[PDB]
């Protein structure tokens, strides 16, 4: 259960891990699943709380 | 530091235990640790190299998880484990070989390489499985300020200095009186010689003192001692101290008399041994003082009477014998010996990629020159290098 | 092969960790492994021996099942465990004894004894366990042609030989010149001797070269080098190269000049050392070349010039000696050492029942004659017998 | 007795496998073992010391239970564990220190300290987590009387006695013949000498024999054999066996002929070798007997007829020699070693606090005198103290 | 360890802050700490003393809580506070005195007495208050291997050794050329004397050299350089080296020129100062090597022709000297200073009761002999004793 | 200039006051001061060195606030504080070394190194603990 919990939580479309505001303009990242999304597959460079 | 050793131990146990046809209830802890490690390391970037000839490589952990639900490991699971195991062992070999050849003139105990600096953060400290080897335990206990100890067999601690001393000397070398010693490796061989055979001496007794210090303290030493010098008992001709002349040595061996050996620490008497010739034990010492007296034979046969004349010219020269060997010891600082494959590995991984001589280590990783000027910074650097070598010595043997 | 090691390791763990008082959690993996082994080995029979005077014995496996649910094991559990532990120990001893004395010309890696042939079946592979042991780890590494490694403490690599060569000799035995070298175990001692004292040689310097081959490629070797020899420093008489006449040899020792020692691999200079003594490291080499110079001192003294006369009759002969001792090494093949009882076990089991002289093992496991030549089939057979000896060593010795 | 080893193993595991970052699933069994040990040992008070300068200290046990809830170990858990780890390390160190020096004439196996007396009671038997090291396993096997021994590298069984036997002698010392040999630790050198070159002996052959008995049994022994003497091959002066006069010895070395080496068992031949050099193995023996023959060459070059006059006066004398060493062996009894530090540990602990000489161990813990008369009581007490020394050394290195 | 310092700090703060009339919102946290410490320290018995002449003391703690409701401290509250504070002061003083004198050669960074061992367990850890002094915070920083620092003022770092050497001498001691130096405390005065004023030496310039090796590592040291020896300028009657004769000295001082002072670290040049007298500053050094010159003046006045005659007689000799003093320094280890009373404190407490001493500390804390041989165990023991002394100095003057 | 001394004093107090066992009321003011310091210092990047052999390093404070406990501390909180203490002491040492090696004939009362000038703005004046040395 603890080894599959990360995948289970990522699988749901009604939940998200977190949000980044970044107070700066960013070019939107393109994806195959959705046309134009604010995809951020990492929390690099920003402080986590 | 300890994180790297934990990863190495995990990889070694994975190599040993992940075989086809085993029972999962025997390697469950190892699989759990492996899964935790692969979860932690996933999603990071690393850079290794920079100096010498070590290539600049980029490493990324992107392997998938490993299942634990099968009651018996099969070939598919075996190869799935083995591929990632080989990748990890290559990565750890690369980071170790990067860290080994770098050192600093100050704060040498601290990491210096980029990869070791990065792997010393806070989150990565959530992966530390076991510290069962002697070197890792020594490092951990040293970092906690307690009693350290490294075992050795035939510890190579004596510096190499084949020097001879003369006291009663002549420009033509017709009658001599002095000491010649050879202290190489883990064996000490000394020989006091007199050309007069104590014939014009104060009551036919001539003394010889030899003091040999050690750069570092030793504890729990077993000593092998024999009353015969095995090297200074043959007809030899050696150049004198003048640098342009040679003199002849014609030895005749007697037995040494009043053979006293002193094991002293901090200028205080610790142990004394007289009239004993081997397998003796001294508990704690740092400095060894050997003294002995050469005595004229009180009575002689005609051959000996002819051999030793009361006149000036001599044909043969008397000499006494003594040899001392240290068998086992435990020190507080890392040393080199003839029972560990660490010094050879360090020198090989240094010279293979042509590392230039650093600011502290003399060129070529010479051990006699290094131990001649043993310094605390050198101690820390040697400790770091040897510990990393010992960690590597289990990934690939 | 691996199944036998698994049995030995399981027996060791069972006989060690099964003692009254310990909590059941400490033996969960042991309980599961032992129960699976018992339930899988039952309903079977084996036959061992059938060669020499070994006990030709039949074995049947019909034992029961141990208890599983116990808060704390009482003495009953220990007794019922030991009653089968001893039986398994005897079975493993019989199997290893029957395996060691066998030999074959073709495919020495593969099992040969009928019991081992039957035990190699896949149905027994469920008894497989961890491979923390070093020698079985080497076996597994060599199974897949991965890089191998054996850590040895002064192994007997150089074949035993006390040889001499004369580059200039006449039927008078007064103006000889040449070399004489002794290779015993880990000790190589060379002595370049001359009866002419370089009184006829050009530039007053005589060249001496010596080569030592290694049948197997070594790597990461630590070597002690001393410029003072002991095997040849005293008067001797040697039978000539005809077996009919004997000649005399009186040595006088000087310091050898331009002492060059080079370790080469495949014909290129890998490592070189000159005017350096003590400890050296060679990363990878197979050929050892030592070149030195007999150098007569320029100026002398009344007590020295007599023993090197320019005239024809000679009485003292110059000799320069070098000694070399490997201490720790890593080898890519299995070689017998001088620090373990594996070779001792092999020789003891071979001589305990007078096995007939086979086609691949020279009689009596004579190490002097075995290393004289070398073939891959010999390597396979030696590795098999050594790993079976290692399995035996962890059991009753 | 085994309870102490279990405690030491538990303490080592608790100190090495309990740090920050380790997932609890790795050390769950150790947690259960520690909880059981702390529960059972709680509430009982011990005392140590009471002899010599060893301090007298009390003991108490009131400690909480280590947690079992957190998924991964945290720093608070580390400190809570390490406090009790430190206290228990001090306790076991003092216990073994007290148990070392105390000794008895009868019941050497029986523990002599009240701490051990209460340790082996009927209530403390619940903590026996492991018995896997060589010495503890051998102790258990000898408690159950199953034949098993130790592993020795470079063992020391031969006492020191530089003894020489003169078969034929005269006060003139112009014609002598006899055997001179030295036993020193792991090395034996024998030199057979004749002053007449056996020119006045039947068939120009001289017989020589030498016998050395052992105080215990050796099996599966590795022997290095060399045909050259090293210690008696240079000129020497030795006081007479009567102590009244002194003679002179000037040898010349020939290769010994018909070199016969015999390994006898209870006076019966088991392993024999002739004209073999290098490495030999003996399956089982207790008495060592060497034989060699000095043979004057039938044909001699003019350089040999200068030192072998068939008349009465003599100037140089013939001598042959053999070299015997023990590399490895497996012994059923208990003996000191060279690759470990147990004997050094015992000597250090005895001589540090100035404990008077007991009725069993000879003064100064001298190995030569102690092994000279290996009485069964001395053997059992030595085994017990060596096991205690290993137990201590596993904790403090 | 820190618990004793916390007790000292809380007692001092209570004694200098709990005075009638103060507002209650100023010592609330201190009173909370005091009450919690009293709660945590109740019901535990302690035994102190039992070594040497130090009396054996017993301690029992049983007291109620203080008051926390008043807003202005009055006579009753301060009276009760002082009543309990006196008892706590007695406890701290006696515990520190008992724990101070005890010494050991093993783990000299661990508690040594019963009181400290019992007071460093898990339960008594909730009384630590702060680390405001310098020695205790240095202890804490060194405990977890951080950079160590210490501020000293004119510390006694150089040992005491009044020895001299002569380069050119005579059997009757009338014409000499050599060096003298008095190294004591933190003062270095090296003087060179030439009787002949360099009339036989080339270039009329005579060079004197001297090396002073410090026993530890310093950092950020200020050095005052007075270019005139204050000592080696008065008439002297000094005993010679052999101790059989004494010779006369009538020096006359000449100013030195080309003064070179160098500071080397790890056998390498770091800082170079030339011909700059007064104040100099160095960053880090381990060995001080001084090289200066003496030059015969070219032209002289009628008052100088009688000073240095080129003729045979000599009665007044050219002499130079350099004064080197350290006015402040910072070290990584601990050394006896001149601004505080640590060494005086330990010497007084040790000599008041005359504790028997072993091979741990030098006899009577002789500072010169202590600096002579400096083993790390001695350093750790001295550091611990100095820290305990610093704790003691906080409460009892 | 005062901000650097405030940092040094508060770092010494945090290192030498927060040890396991102490009561919570003993570190209340220090805890709040550290909280305010972390709030003020986060985000504002800084650069040190740039002259001579002193390496040109960068600093970007990315530390969260500290926790608390009613009865007594736990060692995890201690090490969480200690890591931030290490980062801050490294930063202070680097900026002090940078400030040491700049000087000019013009009025030296004003700060010289850019790091101190950027620190000496009004925006970071709230972190001024005490001036007792």
Image: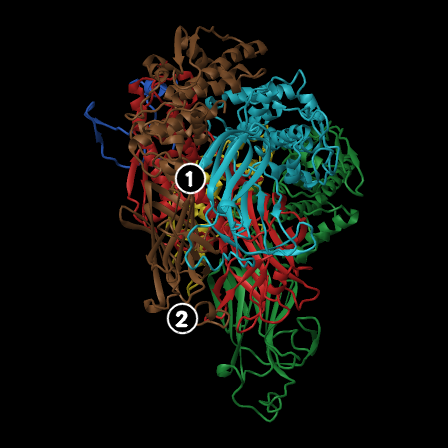
Chain colours: A blue, B red, C brown, D cyan, E green, F yellow
The residue that label 1 is drawn on is C155
Q: Is residue B279 above or below residue E327?
A: above
Q: Is residue D83 above or below residue D250?
A: above
Which quadrant of the structure image shows residue E244?
bottom right
**Residue lying at 39% horizontally and 21% vertically, measured from the top left:** C99
Q: Secondary structure at mark 2?
A: loop
Direction from residue C61 to residue C82 in the image, left or right? right
Q: Mark 2 Cα within 10 Å, few/some/many (few <14, many 20+)?
A: few
**Residue lying at 68% horizontally and 26% vertically, measured from the top left:** D108
**Residue lying at 48% horizontally and 22% vertically, measured from the top left:** C395
Residue C24 is marked as: none
Q: Is residue C248 above or below residue E48?
A: below
- Place of residue E90 in the rendered image (x, y in percent of width and height, measured from the top left): 77, 39
Nearest the camera: E193 or E216?
E193
User: Is there any visible trace of residue B332 in the rendered image?
Assistant: no
User: Is there any visible trace of residue C48 in the rendered image?
Assistant: yes
Marks 2 and 1, the one that precedes in the sequence: 1
């Amino acid at each position: 259960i603890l080894m599959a919990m990360d995948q289970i939580e990522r699988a749901s479309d009604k939940i998200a891990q977190g949000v980044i505001i970044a107070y700066r303009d960013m070019q939107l990242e393109r994806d195959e699943m959705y046309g134009y999304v604010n995809i951020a597959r990492n929390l690099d460079g920003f402080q986590q709380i | 530091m300890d994180v790297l050793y934990s990863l190495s131990k995990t990889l070694k146990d994975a190599r040993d235990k992940i075989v086809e046809g085993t029972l999962y209830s025997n390697v469950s802890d190892l699989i759990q640790q492996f899964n935790q490690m692969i979860i932690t390391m996933n999603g990071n970037e690393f850079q290794t190299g920079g100096i010498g000839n070590l290539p600049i490589r980029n490493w990324n952990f992107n392997f998938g998880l490993l299942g634990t639900t099968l009651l018996n490991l099969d070939a598919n699971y075996v190869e799935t484990a083995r591929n990632t195991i080989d990748y990890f062992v290559d990565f750890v070999d690369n980071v170790c070989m990067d860290e080994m050849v770098r050192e600093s003139q100050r704060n040498g105990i601290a990491p210096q390489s980029d990869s070791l600096r990065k792997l010393s953060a806070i989150k990565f400290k959530r992966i530390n499985f076991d510290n069962s080897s002697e070197y890792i335990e020594n490092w951990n206990l040293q970092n906690r300020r307690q009693r350290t100890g490294f075992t050795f067999h035939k510890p190579n601690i004596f510096p190499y200095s084949a020097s001879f001393t003369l006291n009663r000397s002549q420009p033509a070398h017709d009658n001599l009186m002095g000491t010649m010693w050879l202290n190489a490796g883990s064996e000490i061989q000394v020989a006091g010689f007199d050309y007069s055979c104590a014939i014009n001496a104060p009551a036919n007794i001539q003394q010889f003192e030899h003091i040999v210090p050690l750069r570092r303290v030793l504890t729990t030493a077993t000593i092998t001692l024999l009353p015969d010098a095995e090297r200074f008992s043959f007809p030899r001709v050696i150049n004198s101290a003048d640098g342009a002349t040679t003199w002849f040595f014609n030895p005749v061996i007697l037995r040494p008399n009043n053979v006293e050996v002193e094991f002293l620490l901090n200028g205080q008497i610790i142990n004394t041994y007289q009239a004993r010739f081997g397998t003796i034990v001294a508990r704690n010492f740092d400095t060894i003082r050997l003294s002995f007296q050469l005595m004229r034979p009180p009575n002689m046969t005609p051959a000996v009477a002819v051999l030793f004349p009361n006149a000036q010219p001599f044909e043969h020269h008397a000499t006494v014998g003594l040899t001392l060997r240290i068998e086992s010891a435990v020190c507080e600082s890392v040393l080199a010996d003839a029972s560990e494959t660490l010094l050879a590995n360090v020198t090989s991984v240094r010279q293979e990629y042509a590392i230039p001589v650093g600011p502290v280590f003399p060129p070529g990783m010479n051990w006699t020159d290094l131990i001649t000027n043993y310094s605390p910074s050198r101690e820390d650097n040697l400790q770091r290098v040897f510990t990393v070598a010992s960690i590597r010595s289990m990934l690939i043997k």
